Amino acid sequence: GSSGSSGSYYDILGVPKSASERQIKKAFHKLAMKYHPDKNKSPDAEAKFREIAEAYETLSDANRRKEYDTLGHSAFTSGKGQSGPSSG
Image 1 (cartoon, helix red, strand yellow):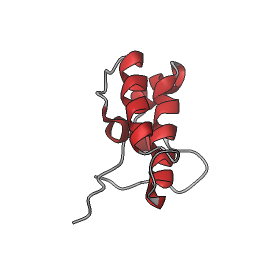
Image 2: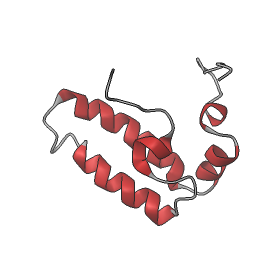
Image 3: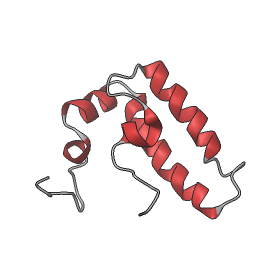
Image 4: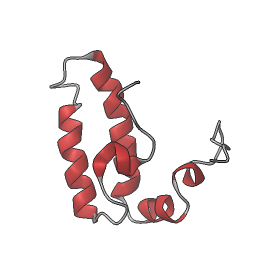
């Protein structure tokens, strides 16, 4: 099947649920580079990075990351838009 198993930030970035602030930014940074538009030529890169960044922003701050950890992926991502009510 496809080769793009995404979902939770921790996955997109590749950091543990208890990853330290330094670990999160550390992992992301490296990634952003591999998917950076300035380096990456492929058109998909630009898009991919669009998911890596947003993922970090949340796991970058304190409260932001605290919520995404106390609520969850689909939980924290429940505002004004289409969510994933899927049971499991």
